[PDB]
């Protein structure tokens, strides 16, 4: 039986800057690769994001990573970061969420 090769994390898809009207939902998504599989965490202006009704975080076996914000408010207007790390290294991608006020 063969095993996967050890490779530091890397994103094949990175998160994108978004503009969302206040009150509506917003989602950041990216895809990570690496072996051992990496552990992932999200940051809002470099502060760890904790799972909640407001911040839904998903990470599946295929490496799809996402952060969904259900009702965007002023406090969400920020820089978000998805960081992935395994024993061989780390990878991060960042993007801005601009909350639009009509």
Image (tube, rainbow, N blue to C red):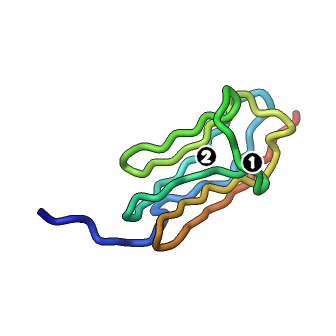
Task: Say which residue appears at 67% left-offset and 56% top-offset.
Answer: 81
Q: Secondary structure at mark 1?
A: strand
Q: In the picture, residue 66 is in which quadrant? A: top right
Q: Are marks 1 and 2 in contact (CB under 8 Å)?
A: yes
Q: In the picture, residue 23 is in which quadrant? A: top right
Q: Is residue 85 left or right of residue 6?
A: right
Say above or below: 72 vs 94: above
| Residue lying furthest front | 87
Task: Say which residue appears at 61% left-offset and 42% top-offset.
Answer: 67
Q: Nearer the viewer, residue 29 or 58?
A: 58
Q: Secondary structure at mark 2?
A: strand
Say above or below: 84 vs 71: below
Provide residue 36's location: percent of width, then percent of height: 38, 62
Q: Is residue 31 left or right of residue 45?
A: left
* Circle number at residue 97: 1
Q: Nearer the viewer, residue 94 or 84?
A: 84
Residue under label 2: 28
Task: Say which residue appears at 64% left-offset and 50% top-offset.
Answer: 42
Task: Say which residue appears at 80% left-offset and 41% top-offset.
Answer: 76
Q: Residues within 10 Å of mark 1 (few under 14, many from 20)?
A: many
Say above or below: 95 vs 55: below
Provide residue 72's location: percent of width, then percent of height: 76, 33
Quadrant in which the N terminus is drawn:
bottom left
């Amino acid at each position: 039986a063969e095993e996967k090769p050890h490779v530091k994390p890397y994103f094949t898809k990175t998160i994108l800057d978004m503009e969302v009207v206040e009150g509506s939902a917003a989602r950041f998504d990216c895809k990570v690769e690496g072996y051992p599989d990496p552990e992932v965490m999200w940051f809002k202006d470099d502060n760890p994001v904790k799972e909640s009704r407001h911040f839904q975080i998903d990470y599946d076996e295929e490496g799809n990573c996402s952060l969904t914000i259900s009702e965007v408010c002023g406090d969400d207007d920020a820089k978000y970061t998805c960081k992935a790390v395994n024993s061989l290294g780390e990878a991060t991608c960042t993007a801005e969420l601009l909350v639009e006020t009509m």
